[PDB]
Length: 330
Image (cartoon, rainbow, N blue to C red):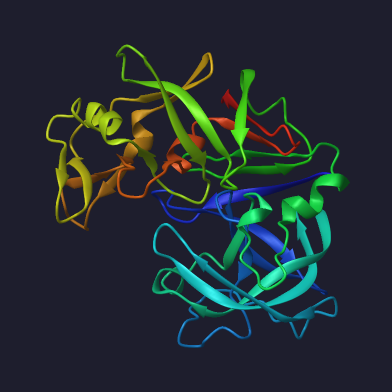
């Protein structure tokens, strides 16, 4: 079996992307934030504290005939953004782009953070990291991808994020129609439970490429590109007016300025993010300070290849057990 679903970003800066998903019987469709750096499928729900639900669409597990309590089961997550969520767990039929998975753990929130509560578009998260991360106690649960894998023609999915534009999540197959040239597959370390890989270096604009291993995670769940202090210094040094700010908490530049592109090495191949991608606009409404899309990783303890980087390449999460991350141009 295969499935493809259209993912659409949620505002003009492409802060996150949402993918529609069918849960229950009959079907309740929720826009989920596909997160390859977490391992929980959770949704706003019926149980969710009504001081904490907005225009978000809610999962009502009393209207699903496929839906059942996982009695005693409980979850609690923390995000690198400080994000906070928790509640109790159900098992229901979940469909993505016509790939049905039965008896999927659907983790219904009783409690959600300010972050999620102020986020109209997003209705919950679908984690596509490795199952060792999933938070549910006391019987730890599996991902949607974990549940789909054997049913799949191939045990892969692809991520093809758009810049100011929808794109696609494909499960089971690779569109040889979506990318240009060759896919360069690189080794994945599954130890931390991340899509965790080792980049072969970088260049800024038309500069010379420095060979140097950057260990980072592929994370569709993070907006920005998080790199180490050395690398991000060399980038923003090429932008006149670019400074690191105490208050705002990150590199800003003047909006009138010019972003030179960023290149990252995937073995022998090279992926340009063009400089357009790195402009995340003004720090506040009216401000002529704009916010940069490449920030230092020094404060979080891992380097994250988030949307800025992934949305410049056609990525493939090979979920074999020699698991392999592929990049191509698009």
